[PDB]
Length: 83
Ligand code: NA
Image (cartoon, rainbow, N blue to C red; front, side, top):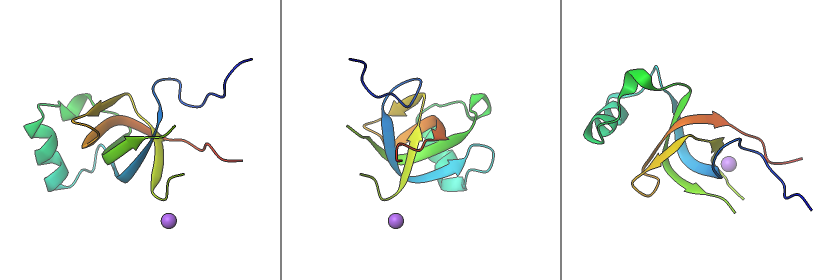
């Protein structure tokens, strides 16, 4: 029948690291600048080195956008796909 659903949009991502969009470190801010992502328009979390799931030992999040094969994700919120 219906398949299981979690994120309203996109797949569940497994991200090595997540950061508050309003407290990014200087390295992450620079990388986003390099990608021409406008930081002031971001909400929630930024994920770095993210891959979509179809098991994750790091952070499982739902994101609005993924860039450069998951180097950076934006609009990410924590999600719990377990019990
Ligand atoms: Na762990």
